Image (cartoon, coloured by chain):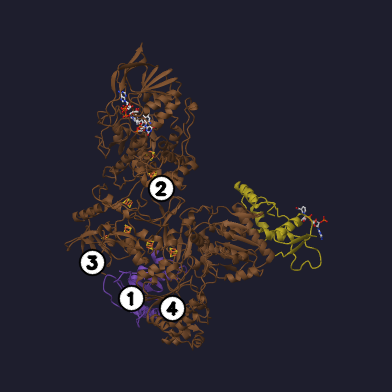
Chain colours: A brown, B yellow, C purple
């Protein structure tokens, strides 16, 4: 004891002996890199990233393999450790092939996750797609409408056909969620700081949006009547609607940002005023000057700049154009001026440019649309002089150029030859370019081109407390460049306001440049969704929109075409985390070799990529030591070491369980699990903790979802052991099934017709009343499924009581295990937590195949486990076992005073002979001090369970800690179903149906009619209600079907097979409208029983169910067991009437006949296994 | 009966009326739970709208035997979703609207043959 | 390491080596009487109120002086422990002089704390 205390990295910490230094440092928030360390298995020592320096040791020690001692001094951030980790990471990055991020995202200036929201649209989740888009910009509809999309240039779908329409999808999502429920991001608590933003263009609005989300108070000073910047006063109305821009700015100003219009800084309000009154200042003034013609007579009346012209068009001012207008320039300003002039009644518009069409910096789409609308292009012509009389410009004398040598930028330089041409024009508009003007703002340094000089990456001007960004710094660019600069400056300002200014730096990713068209030649080809463009006859006269937003069918069709280029493991990969932490270059030299694979492993569940393997060996170690399948292994030496299945066979031809533990321990993207959703994606999923709904083992899970789609399930390594199996890892895809029912249906004239919930409730209540009135008591059977929660089962029992019946049963429970007649409670006498302290485990049945996580736990515990032999499939062999145990000298007096009928049990074993193997098993069992018997309920009959109870009772190994019988139930809530009274055998139900006693049946979650005997039985009923998720075989035979929700949409509790009550939480909202508890509550309220919430039902459970005392305030986040919160049963005597174990004779029971699956979810999983 | 008047309509109308400021106290029988003198003392006026809630008997020999029940009581137990017993054959005595409602509700409640006397 | 786990009073608990059974039970909300135990000094063994029954031991052990081991079964509410604690408390109450509550409060029918508010 004495408080073992270590000193690491300067701090003094109190730890526990036996722990490694890695665990001890991580418990106290000290981060040490590791790749090959798992705390549940032995150390390996492959990566070497966990090296620390320990005083008294000449060489670096691996903190994953050294246990803590008392008073040892550890340093983790020295020069030697950092050098070793950087060298190791460089060597690892020397061998890695993959795309951390897709080409589309890396081509975007703002690094928007294009793959993420494209793949979220492909899943039908649009609010999530908008939430993903809004992490980078505040105005996605305008940007999606007007972006020149560099992302679509880099799209890899271009190697198959034309690429994905990323901007159109973004505009669709943004407008759909503007016209519906508007999304407001969460905001940090107020910090008490003040930031003044000058200008309300894209940069200023983005900086204000991202500083308000940090908790600061932002005020925007705009010189114009309305916000938007050049998006409002330079973008024409037919390309960008101003209603969209106004609606977005209103959404932003709802968040608490104040915008003050008609306030020009330096002309109306000084910058010193803002410097004194605010904690920071950001300058997003933009470039709001127009370049002149730079020719003779450029100052004459009749010549006006393009920016000024567009501004007067926007403000609905009085302009003069004339019949003929000459636009000088070739960029987007010239295109906008020319097309606005065509709409403003100019009869002929001509564009004067000094180069060719292919040399123009304008977009080809804009040029094509302009040519369609009617503007003529005059090429390779440079203006020289403006001619006019009486001060009114009337002609443009220009020089004729010729193509010359390319410049440094890759464009040919025009050269005059000898020729001039004079063009007649009423108006001459110079759309030559833009220049930044600082105006009257003083003490701000500017470049020779007018741009504000800032410190690169810190966005700081010469004046303190003042920052700059946008077109004021970079000059004229596209809008997403301004948005990116605004967001980066917002981050830098936010860091500065906390007292430590850090500059913005780009991140390092692994990228692939070897992808060619031949590598994608197996992809099918699907044509792009073309844009609906209005005819050019009506476009030339109106300022109406020239294109339409995508519909939902078009958006789904376009989004389902993505190739999913980026790594799915990016948000959880540990290689890229350390690569970016230690700043290792991911660039590759061509003179070194990385192994490239042509792998073909089309396993339906597990994907293996040897190109992304760091050879930590965690997968083979887990599959060997934990699972025990040993389906994969190492092959080779040195560089040629590769992990692959047995004999290089496919993973489907080997002993794989498809558990997915190799996926769960992998630190990189070498092992991934397959997609549960319609199209999986790399995303930060939301996680909800629940329990598995397939086995009685009750493994804890984390459901990872995004909106209303469940994407994956991971083990819960914090609250449990962190293991799963195939049904728990991959079994929650039925939540995403499109074949699930949505509304109740009633059979009229032999057709199912949809009804409302009230009509369905009235119909089922009245029909049950009709059956009771015609046929009296006990004419209704209630058959439930043991997959429902405890509250659902309690309400089903109440419903059975309300319609005057005692036949409550289940096809899966089928009467219990028979342990209740012997001991008193039909439950296991010990918990799973006591499996580690036994010195002998006797396994009866196929525990490994049915409940494999239990076998994982038993194997990792390391105790001696002996399986019951398969050649002893007769009960007479068990009687020989009892005789051999009795001949080994048990205490007859204690078992005589504690049991009933031990004398007859001794008499019936009088002439029983004992074989050699039976003697060996009995000696092994009776020798051990604390043995456990683990009985698998699926493959073991009731008499074998009774005989194991007899052995444990007569030996004396029951009713104590680490000694007794563990019984593993078939379904998740079989224990809860047994506790609520669903213990009637189904032979009684079949006999009552065929004898005319039972006329109606209520089936909840089961499918008995998949087999012909029960189907012909159900054909003789009078009425049948089926509560199920799918329209299965039984629901087709019903007179009424009511839908049920999946386990990812329910709140409740499940009782484990070791009597532990666990909380089940709802990941996603119910897709049918109502949950099962609500349906049962409404029906019971119709029948006359009043419950309101689940708390009332839990109080009723605690008051009525005998052994569940304490469920009202149990706090199921901790461990709750129902008998007095006790792990061990019968510590004070058995639960029978006389407090004695009832030992009675058992007949000769032949070899077991395998049981059937009646739950619809189980058979859905089984049938879907064959589909892949 | 429910097939002629939906109770959802009646509940919605009464909710509309109780939005106006009228308090309705259920499960309170005047004279059995609360005296009429109490209401006389505590209120400025009292209105009695108790209705006619008894059923006439058969006025015949053996009318008190088990297996004979009144129409109003039968309809009330049908409405409250209580446990009733009908049998295959049911004889309804009467010719008014009570007899029609009883006979048609009996046809819906699984009676194989209903005859009106 | 290996998760030292004991089983006391029917429950299974995970504890740390070197701790006494008294500390281990009190960490998990199990109340065992004690009068002469201080966790910062050595055990004494005077009162004897901390006696529990441990499997494998013929006589009651003092939980203030026995450290936890792996997989030991402890009961604190048996007949023997309750009898021993009641006898010890009777012998202690055989020698105690004092007023737990003043005469003024014990004479009040509602047992109002007269000394307290006075
Ligand atoms: C004609 C034209 C067409 C364009 N078309 C496209 C296109 O199709 N696609 C695309 O992606 N990009 C396009 N752009 C580019 C895009 O509009 C800009 O690059 C982007 O809006 C830059 O915005 P900003 O925040 O840097 O500054 P701006 O939005 O230009 O201006 C910010 C604000 O600062 C205010 N301001 C200026 N001086 C002061 C002062 N002294 N005090 C207070 N406030 C002040 C102004 O009123 C303005 O509202 C176009 C640009 C122009 C000119
Ligand atoms: N922010 C934006 O939206 C972008 C701007 N534009 C265009 O560029 C302008 C401003 O940006 P930027 O490209 O830096 O501006 P520039 O100064 O490069 O001018 C751009 C256009 O004008 C031509 N030009 C420039 N000076 C003269 C002169 N004395 N005589 C004749 N032609 C000239 C250029 O052709 P050349 O090809 O020979 O250089 C090009 O057509 C905008 O007004 C617009 O017309 C276009 C795309 C993006
Ligand atoms: N409020 C309502 O909705 C109205 C009531 N009803 C019927 O009338 C009943 C109560 O109203 P009211 O008309 O004043 O009641 P009555 O006392 O007049 O009885 C009405 C019905 O019962 C018959 N009847 C009465 N006494 C006997 C008896 N000893 N033997 C056989 N048949 C008998 C009547 O037929 P006869 O024609 O020979 O009088 C008639 O069918 C209701 O139960 C209902 O059956 C019908 C219409 C309106
Ligand atoms: S903002 Fe522009 S570059 Fe970025 S994803 Fe959208 S269309 Fe592509
Ligand atoms: S195919 Fe999909 S993931 Fe690949 S670049 Fe195009 S949009 Fe991005
Ligand atoms: S496994 Fe990790 S490092 Fe490798 S490409 Fe994927 S995210 Fe990047
Ligand atoms: S596949 Fe994954 S777990 Fe296995 S060695 Fe490679 S990186 Fe490690
Ligand atoms: S899924 Fe399980 S059994 Fe299959 S290779 Fe991975 S760890 Fe081994
Ligand atoms: S062992 Fe049973 S409870 Fe655990 S994950 Fe597998 S099916 Fe689910
Ligand atoms: S060498 Fe210790 S974590 Fe890899
Ligand atoms: S506390 Fe007194 S003997 Fe242990």
CA gap between label 4 and label 1 equals 26 Å
Residue A59 located left or right of residue A550 = left
Dot placed on the residue nearer the N-terminal end, 3 or 2: 3
Residue A687 located left or right of residue A41 = right
At numbered mark 2, what does the secondary structure look like: helix, strand or loop? loop
Of tags 1 and 2, the one toward the viewer is 2
CA gap between label 2 and label 4 equals 64 Å
**Residue denoted by label 2:** A522
Of tags 3 and 1, the one toward the viewer is 3
Residue A775 located left or right of residue A329 = right
Mark 4 belongs to chain:
A
Mark 1 belongs to chain:
C
CA gap between label 1 and label 2 equals 73 Å
Of tags 3 and 2, the one toward the viewer is 2
Q: Are marks 4 and 1 on the same chain?
A: no
Q: Is residue B70 above or below residue A495?
A: below
**Residue denoted by label 1:** C63
The x and y percentages for residue A701 are 42, 60
**Residue denoted by label 4:** A958
**Residue denoted by label 3:** A69
Query: Mark 3 packing: few (<14 Cα in 10 Å), some, or many (20+)?
Result: some
The x and y percentages for residue A348 are 43, 20
Dot placed on the residue nearer the N-terminal end, 2 or 4: 2
Extreme-top residue of the structure: A390
Q: Is residue C7 above or below residue A895?
A: above
Q: Is residue A1163 at least partly visible in the picture?
A: yes
CA gap between label 4 and label 3 equals 41 Å
Which of C56 and A706 lies nearest the eye of the viewer?
Answer: A706
Residue A2 is drawn in which quadrant? bottom left
Which of A695 and C83 lies nearest the eye of the viewer?
Answer: A695
């Amino acid at each position: 004891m004495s408080k073992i205390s270590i000193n690491i990295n300067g701090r003094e910490l109190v730890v526990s002996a036996g722990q490694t230094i890695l665990q001890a440092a991580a418990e106290h928030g000290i981060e040490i890199p590791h790749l090959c360390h798992d705390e549940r298995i032995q150390p390996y020592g492959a990566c070497g990233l966990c090296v620390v320096e320990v005083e008294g040791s000449p060489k670096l020690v691996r903190s994953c393999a050294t246990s803590v001692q008392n008073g040892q001094v550890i340093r983790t951030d020295t020069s030697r450790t950092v050098v070793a980790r950087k060298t190791a990471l460089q060597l690892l990055a020397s061998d890695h092939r993959g795309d951390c991020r897709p080409p589309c995202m890396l081509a975007c200036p703002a690094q928007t996750d294009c793959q993420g929201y494209v793949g979220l649209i492909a899943n039908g989740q649009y609010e999530e797609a908008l939430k993903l888009i809004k992490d980078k910009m505040p105005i996605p509809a305008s940007i999606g409408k007007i972006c020149p999309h560099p992302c679509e240039t880099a799209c890899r779908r271009e190697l198959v056909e034309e690429p994905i329409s990323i901007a159109q999808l973004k505009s669709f999502v943004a407008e759909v969620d503007l016209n519906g429920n508007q999304y407001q991001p969460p905001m940090k608590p107020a910090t008490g700081k003040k930031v003044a933003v000058v200008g309300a263009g894209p940069a200023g609005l983005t900086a204000a949006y991202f500083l308000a989300r940090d908790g600061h108070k932002v005020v925007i000073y705009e010189a114009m009547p309305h916000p938007g910047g050049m998006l409002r006063y330079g973008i024409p109305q037919y390309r960008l609607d101003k209603a969209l821009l106004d609606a977005e700015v209103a959404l932003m100003t709802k968040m608490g940002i104040e915008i003050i219009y008609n306030t020009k800084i330096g002309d109306d309000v000084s910058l010193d005023y803002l410097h004194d009154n605010y904690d920071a200042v950001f300058l997003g003034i933009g470039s709001w000057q127009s370049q002149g013609l730079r020719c003779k007579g450029e100052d004459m009346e009749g010549v006006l700049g393009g920016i000024d012209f567009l501004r007067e068009v926007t403000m609905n001012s009085n302009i003069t154009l004339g019949g003929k207008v000459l636009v000088v320039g070739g960029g987007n300003t010239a295109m906008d001026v020319a097309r606005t002039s065509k709409r403003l009644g100019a009869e002929e518009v001509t564009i004067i440019y000094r180069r060719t069409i292919d040399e123009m910096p304008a977009e080809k789409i804009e040029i094509h649309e302009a040519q369609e609308e009617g503007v003529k292009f005059q090429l390779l012509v440079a203006p020289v002089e403006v001619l006019g009389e009486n001060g009114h410009a009337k002609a443009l004398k220009c020089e004729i150029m010729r193509l010359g040598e390319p410049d440094a930028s890759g464009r040919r330089k025009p050269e005059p030859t000898g020729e001039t041409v004079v063009y007649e024009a009423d108006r001459i508009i110079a759309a030559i370019g833009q220049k930044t003007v600082i105006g009257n703002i003083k003490d701000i340094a500017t470049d020779k081109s007018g741009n504000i000089i800032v410190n690169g990456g810190a966005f700081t001007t010469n004046r303190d407390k003042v920052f700059a960004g946008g077109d004021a710094v970079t000059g004229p660019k596209i809008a997403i460049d301004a948005i990116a600069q605004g967001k980066n400056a917002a981050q830098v300002i936010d860091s500065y306001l906390n007292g430590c200014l850090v500059p913005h730096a780009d991140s390092q990713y692994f990228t692939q440049k070897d992808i060619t068209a031949a590598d994608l030649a197996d992809r099918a080809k699907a044509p792009r969704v073309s844009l609906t463009v209005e005819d050019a006859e009506v476009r030339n006269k109106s300022f109406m929109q020239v294109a339409k937003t995508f519909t939902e069918e078009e958006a789904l069709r376009e989004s389902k075409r993505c190739l999913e280029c980026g790594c799915r493991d990016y948000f959880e990969c540990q290689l890229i985390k350390y690569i970016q932490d230690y700043d290792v270059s991911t660039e590759k030299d061509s003179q070194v070799e990385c192994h490239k694979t042509t792998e073909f492993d089309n396993h339906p569940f597990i994907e293996r990529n040897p190109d992304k393997c760091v050879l930590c060996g965690l997968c083979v170690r887990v599959c060997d030591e934990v699972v025990g399948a040993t389906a994969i292994g190492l092959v080779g030496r040195g560089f040629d070491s590769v992990i692959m299945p047995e004999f290089k066979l496919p993973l489907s031809e080997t002993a794989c369980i498809s558990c997915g533990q190799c996926v769960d321990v992998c630190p990189t993207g070498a092992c991934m699990e397959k997609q549960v959703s319609y199209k999986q994606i790399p995303a930060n999923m939301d996680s909800m903790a629940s329990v598995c709904g397939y086995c009685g083992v009750g493994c804890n899970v984390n459901i990872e979802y995004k909106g209303d789609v469940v994407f994956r399930v991971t083990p819960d390594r914090v609250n449990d052991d962190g293991w799963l199996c195939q049904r728990g890892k991959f079994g929650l895809g039925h939540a995403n099934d499109k074949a699930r029912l949505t509304a109740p249906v009633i059979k009229r004239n032999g057709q199912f017709v949809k009804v409302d919930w009230n009509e369905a409730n009235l119909e089922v209540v009245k029909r049950l009343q009709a059956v009771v009135a015609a046929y009296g008591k006990d004419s209704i059977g209630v058959v439930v499924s043991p997959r429902l929660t405890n509250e659902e089962l309690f309400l089903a029992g109440k419903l059975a009581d309300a319609v005057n019946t005692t036949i409550k049963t289940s096809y899966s429970v089928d009467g219990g295990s028979g342990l209740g007649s012997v001991l008193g409670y039909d439950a296991s006498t010990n918990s799973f937590a006591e499996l580690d302290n036994s010195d002998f485990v006797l396994t009866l049945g196929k525990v490994k195949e049915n409940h494999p996580v239990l076998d994982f736990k038993i194997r990792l515990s390391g105790v001696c486990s002996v399986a019951w032999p398969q050649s002893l499939a007769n009960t007479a062999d068990m009687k020989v076992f009892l005789k051999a145990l009795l001949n080994l000298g048990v205490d007859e007096n204690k078992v005589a005073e504690k049991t009933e009928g031990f004398a007859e049990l001794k008499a019936s074993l009088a002439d029983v002979k004992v074989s050699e193997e039976i003697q060996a098993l009995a000696q092994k069992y009776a020798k051990a001090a604390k043995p456990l018997i683990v009985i698998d309920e699926d493959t073991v009959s009731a008499e074998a369970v009774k005989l194991m109870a007899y052995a444990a009772v007569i030996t004396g190994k029951i009713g104590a800690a680490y000694r007794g019988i563990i019984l593993v139930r078939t379904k998740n809530n079989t224990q809860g179903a047994v506790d609520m009274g669903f213990v009637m055998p189904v032979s009684a139900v079949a006999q009552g149906i065929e004898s005319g006693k039972i006329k109606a049946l209520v089936v909840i979650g089961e499918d008995p009619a998949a087999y012909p005997q029960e189907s012909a039985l159900l054909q003789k009923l009078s009425f049948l209600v089926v509560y199920d998720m799918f329209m299965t075989k039984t629901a087709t035979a019903a007179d009424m079907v009511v839908p049920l929700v999946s386990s990812a949409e329910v709140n409740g509790t499940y009782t484990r097979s070791d009597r532990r009550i666990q909380a089940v939480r709802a990941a996603i909202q119910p897709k049918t409208g109502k949950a099962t508890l609500q349906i049962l509550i409404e029906t019971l309220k119709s029948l006359g029983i009043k419950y309101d919430t689940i708390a009332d039902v839990r109080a009723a459970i605690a008051s009525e169910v005998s052994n569940y005392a304490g469920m009202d305030a149990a706090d199921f986040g901790t461990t709750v067991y129902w008998p007095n919160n006790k792990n061990v049963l019968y510590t004070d005597g058995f639960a029978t009437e006389g407090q004695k174990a009832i030992l009675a004779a058992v007949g000769d029971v032949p070899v077991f006949v395998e049981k059937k699956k009646y739950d619809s979810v189980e058979m859905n999983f089984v049938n879907g296994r064959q589909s892949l």
